Length: 110
Length: 104
Figure 1: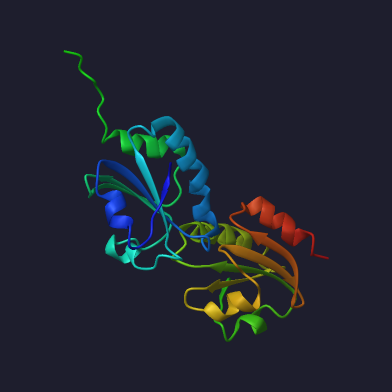
Figure 2: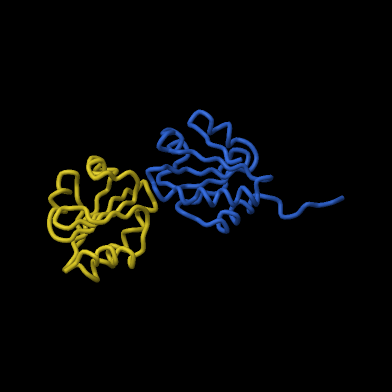
């Protein structure tokens, strides 16, 4: 379940755990190309990664609060802190690489 | 030899001969990808093709007048009539083909 955020909800939605946030807009015909990517990533990683989308056409205030100057821009957040920035289109493999830098490599069994 | 249009000059700049017009904005990263393509097109066929760019963030009137609803959008015009519309990114070869349908 990819979440649709609003200016009002963005903070809460992104504040906890590992989160990939997608700043996009219908007007940037392009930035839509990310949407199927997010679906594949949600299929593969959804247990460990919360995906949040925010349509910056409808939600005009969030971009400025995160220094988003062009769309699309994706962010990786851990516990509400931005830990990666990805400007422009990137394929599933590139975004998987970024997120994985912030997830456990090992799971120790005691 | 690409022309940067404004809302005021757009209709006049695209009114004659074969024209490729690019609707883009710095705010849209995919729209910027069109630029090197246009430079290559100009190098290849600049004597037969006029290329006009319009930054819709600084010139928002023109997008409405041409029914542009997302960016980028490219138009081919012949003597001021829109004869092809291309929504989204397309590579040089695809745009070259669109224009070539309107030469001669």
